[PDB]
Image (cartoon, rainbow, N blue to C red; front, side, top):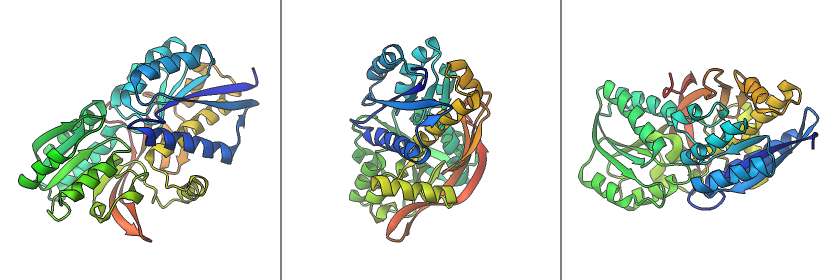
Length: 364
């Protein structure tokens, strides 16, 4: 048992956010295919548990992994409440909690053992806020999922956009579970703002765009902006021409021109027959952090040693250069602005702007 290192992966494999857990599970499989399953004399075992994005299930499964399976690390957490539900047990058992998906700013402050490899909504939202203001968009209506990351997206977009002389004319919120976009989009057809600012979690953008095109807003001259979540690369292949010209700020694009991303995407497509999205890259880097931490401690598997090793650690990711902030345990990464274009018959988020090494604005 001393030659074994266990990772308890708690992600949604079923339900609304199933696409998140599918991507993270896949990326981790690929990382192991490409790097092996052994570091510092320890055989890594990933134990997968489907919480179906229900926080009550996340707590039960995290307790079951830590106490019964005696995992060294817990990872994943598709939504913010899933991450928050597991934080007390991570703190009590001194087990690192690797947040590979959830994007609310405060998450890292809720446990000293939390480290994040995904993003915060504030990171992207401040950038699209500034861009919209500087690009002649004056009147914006917002649609944001009615929970923590959506509130973060809205608050940070609003702050930067209004400081640039923009006006928010309407604020609309929809549930995380089975949102209906029709009423808001009908409101958009009558009251016509310059753009809509839209946040919906990974896996939902396809449904938004489907209803967007059905209400014919593609011709209305209302631009679509926001953080990249709506323009999920896992979903872009299914979207029609209405998505063309949608401008988002985000930390990852499948079209990121780097050699490592070229290699990552090709390998992902070959192995799974699908384009990887931003959730996949969150898992891929989450498990890299686990591998590289064990290497740096020389096999020491206790929580304190791992966290200390994880802090300040920097590497190149398919998304670009990233690092774990030694002070906050949150991810410091580039934020890009992208435009949806068609290349070789496929829609891509094409990066045209780059902001270097953005710390979470929710903590700065």
